[PDB]
Length: 57
Length: 63
Image (tube, rainbow over all chains, first blue to last red; front, side, top):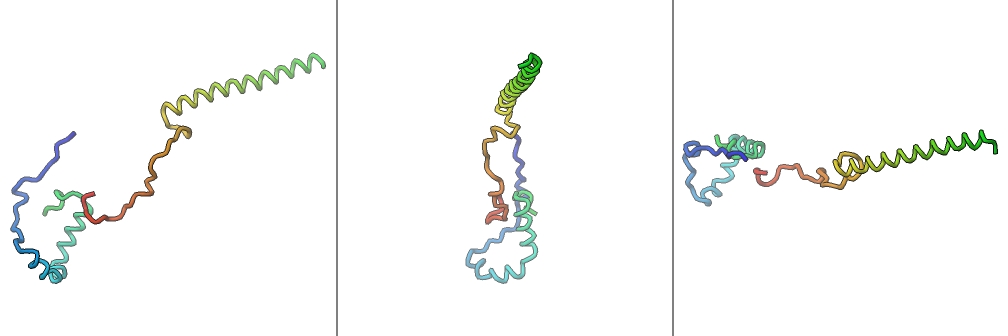
């Protein structure tokens, strides 16, 4: 069949959130209140597109 | 019986039996075509009902 099309490594470069899981869980409820809108844009895009390559930006 | 009666009764018998024979030949041909192509109401061996599929958003998105 066809060739699967993957994004390049430049498309995956981003400033990673390099904090530990306790730093994430301690800051979790304020992250869920304050970072609501692009997170829900992303997860709606992620359950509608069903393809992570269409959900990168 | 009159020869008229036997004669016309024989014509009636021959029409009924010729119709039944042509219908049996058509029945054989119809059964052969429906087993071969599977497009008629006969030989419809069952598949999975698609009403059983859960179309809800699942726990993970890649599906």
